[PDB]
Image 1 (cartoon, each protein chain N blue to C red):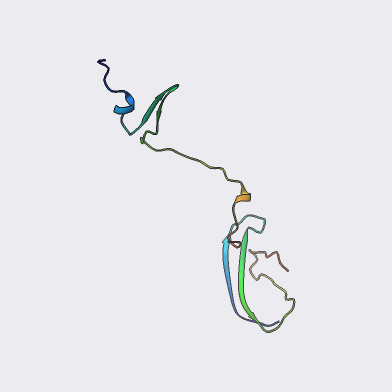
Image 2: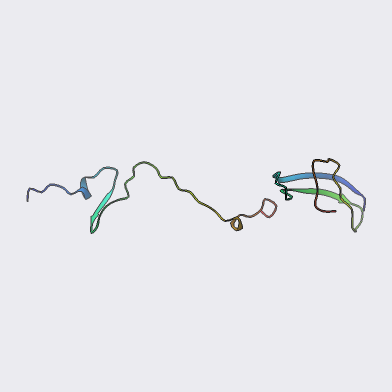
Length: 49
Length: 49
């Protein structure tokens, strides 16, 4: 009864919360390095473009 | 063939031992036929004879 509000409603950075298992999801916090290794077959030559 | 109004453009170059550069020559030529090509600068070798 005296419970208060869940993290789903109160948590910072706009994040959603779920419990089976527990996750914080989609926090708009910080930034993410992403790195790609691209096979040479994928690129088209400056004379072909 | 006799050639005139020639312009030479270099889409990309890399000094890569393997013909790592490619060049497009725009031209006007008097008649149809085979024609020889050569490089006058010793530091640049062209593959096509």
